[PDB]
Length: 49
Length: 49
Ligand SMILES: [Mg+2]
Image (cartoon, rainbow over the protein chains, first blue to last red):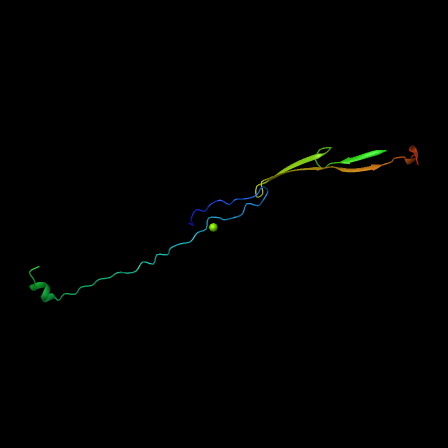
């Protein structure tokens, strides 16, 4: 939503002017964060951990 | 001599009010429809200077 404003100083009998609540968005665009690791079968067998 | 009074609502003077919320003015309006006709104009004499 738009910021709050100050009401307007006006004459008598004058039109009340429009300054309506105005809207926008922030767009999220979720980015795929990825991580890989590869290990050989002999490595997996021989390692202590 | 006949005074002919027409009103769309009721029989006599119609008063209407309005509130203007854009300008903060109240109005009062009045209306009547009127004619006048002689049924016999030979029933009347004018005095001329
Ligand atoms: Mg503004």
